[PDB]
Image (cartoon, rainbow over all chains, first blue to last red; front, side):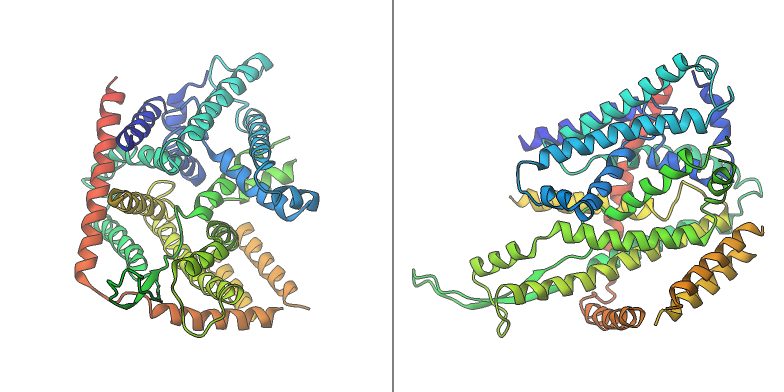
Length: 401
Length: 98
């Protein structure tokens, strides 16, 4: 039933959070180190896959990274632009081709690690050495783990609710929290962490969430009017009902997307010592710099336009309005109403993603001032508040049905 | 009219200054912005100005201060955060324990 869908997904993600040749203690030592902020970012994105040293080390990050790629192939390769627009059939072959790009990306990324990261039994461990039998068993275990997570997420998007992967990493970071807060209050009895600053970070967290929910309070409701008299004579009004159109959608898609595209090139590309210029560029690619977050922002807003344009299909919505019997007096139905809702929704959602990028940027300055890294992050606070809000609104919404 | 983005590039490189190679890269990207500005930019300006009129139009749909809906949201997110934390504790305490 409906009760069993939610308790099946819940059970699936509970054995996911239990399951989520490398001496892992060494890594646990390596994650106490600054100057590679992105490692801590990988444990957020992994919600602790490389902190726990999981079997699936980077998670579902390849898959999402394919979903943008194909959208480029919708643009480039018109032969590809015709098969993407070709309707029903063809799309599941494109989804299996997205899967086949994922799989060759997991191969490629395992190459990127075992070329790039290792070359030391600190970065490696004692069983897995620089031999191709150890290399092969490494790649096999990591790709088998990412495949298990891929299949489980192909069963949960379809027969379960929503996304899931978001909540996977999310519960990984919430359950990664209590040690981190134990460390902060141990350093709070030390003068490492000052008590004024730590309650300042707690209140800035609270005020950014307040801003989030303020951006969620007023949405934009377009009052459209229905003059309807049912022929049964129990006729009352000409009723004006607002369409409460909502801002940014179901998981800020370019944030999660952009995060997967941030973390892919810093491991595979920048870690090549043997080439030297490429390694230097990878070293520079550190998120202490404004250039990366600007380019990420520009990416996000453009990608946001695209994703939102994907979400709604305004002609169907408009046809519904003609079907449902409501009218805005004075504007030609169809294309002009279409073009209308489209320009306005673009102009709103763009402002939404803008302010999203603003709430996104400040915690990083907070993380520079405090010394915070991939933990309390400007990307993940927003996504967690919006997943929780979204699911409980969708739960009440589907609880009325 | 691409001028304000290049002034922003000057400001971002100035923020990136205060440890030489990164400030040089920010200056190099500022030079790239000027190279884009060397030759659509005024139409992007007018588009963003239109978008700011649209912004204000969409400000009219922003719900003004209410301490009640603030507290509703507040308590909702506090409750939900407590839920996820209780999930996280019920999982990782006995899992790390095991």
